[PDB]
Image (tube, rainbow, N blue to C red):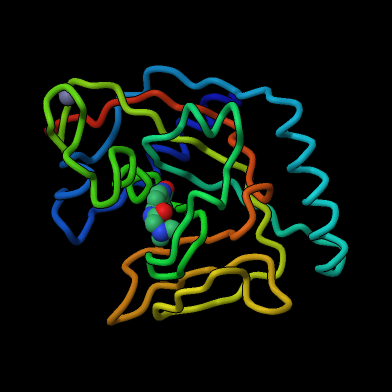
Length: 199
Ligand SMILES: CN(C)CC(=O)Nc1ccc2[nH]c(=O)c3ccccc3c2c1
Ligand SMILES: [Zn+2]
């Protein structure tokens, strides 16, 4: 039921994307192959230490969410953790680590920015054959700065612990959540999956 619950969040948060599947491929659901809980104690403690500190700075409230992350560097993330040193100015919200509440938004990043050239084997952003990996993560948002338009930050806004990108007419289709310190997320579940050709 733990893994079922993860599988339900993955399927149910899929959305139709404005790019027509260009980045992440064309699909309405996934084939979920495997869900593994990552047990990296050094990383868990880094995470909970920071979460305690953020909660102190936010009226005894971590504001933690479970959110998706797609990247080509999933296997480094599970061993070494998220690392803001690999983030550069860019994106809507600058040099942060980005997360989605819609699994299909994160899927757009699994093979690179805008999907890169897709899977290594077939160079196909809509590959139905190769197995993809997404993380489903605990993220400490603390006091989160709501923003609609591009604001390329190096760090959290003063007094804040994250940025939440809200949907807006000339802006985002879907929400996105941005942290500027690697220790504010833990890669809790590693999900191995395929996108499924539509019916
Ligand atoms: C913005 N620069 C720090 C480049 C960059 O890291 N892009 C990037 C890289 C990986 C990303 N992965 C996500 O799951 C995601 C989810 C919602 C919105 C953005 C992303 C996402 C974005
Ligand atoms: Zn492939």
